[PDB]
Image (cartoon, rainbow, N blue to C red):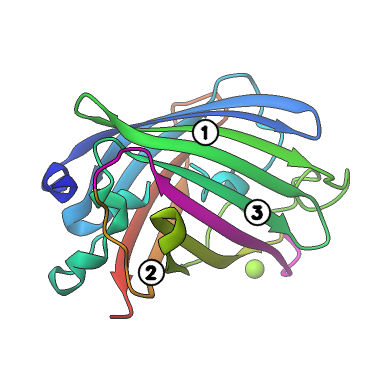
């Protein structure tokens, strides 16, 4: 039944409150998703001033229900199956040789809009490390998100490594460990092992003076 809510274009709202090494900030995002094509278009704004971390470090925190699941994999789409009541998504993002983010989000429908509400806490970042030193390029590599079922929580786990390009040609690794659990009492789809193939393009709105990020993303399920 939840997949029925995604056959057309769906408006998206994202609201994040963050604290990284005591630097407090908020981000508001608006856009739309079209799961038929695994396509997301979003604009995020830092509503509190300057973002204290690089925008690319927030991309995985800032709605995998818009993935394109091929018809032959439709029985493996947990994310849509949990809608409209939604799911809780928790992650730990470990930056190699640096600090970590812990996030908690609720993703659910509010009327006909898909909403992602997030709290992010970052600790033990190095002041002149790649994150607080803002040494990351404004770009995003393509990645696979590996999904496995968590039968005991009636949900799923996801594991992946993000490779963030550093301005000097090196790479900043970020290990991601995520868990999702449904909010409602109805049944959800528990998938076989598979992955999400993601591609993301970051840009700016040339008329915008606030600190912001324009994102175009494609997400396709595969491996089955
Ligand atoms: Mg390079």
Q: Secondary structure at mark 3?
A: strand
Which of pointers 2 and 1 lies earlier in the amino acid sequence? 1
Q: What's the distance in space between the residues labelled 3 and 2, CA to CA?
A: 19 Å
State the residue position of label 3. Answer: 93
User: Tag on residue 197?
Assistant: 2
Vertical position of residue 147 compared to residue 80: above or below? below
Dot 3 alpha-carbon crowd within 10 angstroms: few under 14, some 14 to 19, many 20 or more: many
Vertical position of residue 76 compared to residue 203: above or below? below
**Residue 42: quadrant of the picture:** top left
Residue farthest right in this picture: 127
Residue 164 is situated, as x and y percent measured from the top left of the image, at: 64, 61
Dot 1 alpha-carbon crowd within 10 angstroms: few under 14, some 14 to 19, many 20 or more: many
Residue 98 is situated, as x and y percent measured from the top left of the image, at: 82, 55
Q: What's drawn in magenta, residue-wise?
A: 167-186
Residue occupying the point 37% across, 46% down: 63
Which of pointers 3 and 2 lies earlier in the amino acid sequence? 3
State the residue position of label 1. Answer: 118
Q: Is residue 169 magenta?
A: yes
Q: For this view, does 85 lie left or right of residue 173?
A: left
Residue occupying the point 24% across, 37% down: 84
Residue 154 is situated, as x and y percent measured from the top left of the image, at: 38, 55
Quadrant containing ligand 1 reads: bottom right
For the question of whether residue 205 can be seen, the reply is no
- Image quadrant containing the C terminus: bottom left
């Amino acid at each position: 039944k939840g997949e029925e809510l995604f056959t057309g274009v769906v408006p998206i709202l994202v609201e994040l409150d963050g604290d990284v090494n005591g630097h407090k900030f908020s981000v508001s995002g608006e856009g739309e998703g079209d799961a038929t094509y695994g396509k997301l278009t979003l604009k995020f704004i830092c509503t509190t001033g300057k973002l204290p971390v690089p925008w690319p470090t927030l991309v995985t925190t800032l709605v995998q229900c818009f993935s394109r699941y091929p018809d032959h994999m439709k029985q493996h789409d947990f994310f849509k199956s949990a809608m409209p009541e939604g799911y809780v998504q928790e992650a730990t993002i470990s930056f190699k040789d640096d600090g970590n983010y812990k996030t908690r989000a609720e993703v659910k429908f509010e009327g006909d809009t898909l909403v992602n509400r997030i709290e992010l806490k970052g600790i033990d970042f190095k002041e002149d490390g790649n994150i607080l030193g803002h040494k990351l390029e404004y770009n995003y590599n393509s990645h696979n998100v590996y999904i496995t079922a968590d039968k005991q929580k009636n949900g799923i786990k996801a594991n992946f490594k993000i490779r963030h390009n550093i301005e000097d040609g090196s790479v900043q690794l970020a290990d991601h460990y995520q868990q999702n659990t449904p909010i409602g009492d109805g049944p959800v789809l528990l998938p076989d092992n598979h992955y999400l193939s993601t591609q993301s393009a970051l840009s700016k709105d040339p008329n915008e003076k606030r600190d912001h990020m324009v994102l175009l993303e494609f997400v396709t399920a595969a491996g089955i």
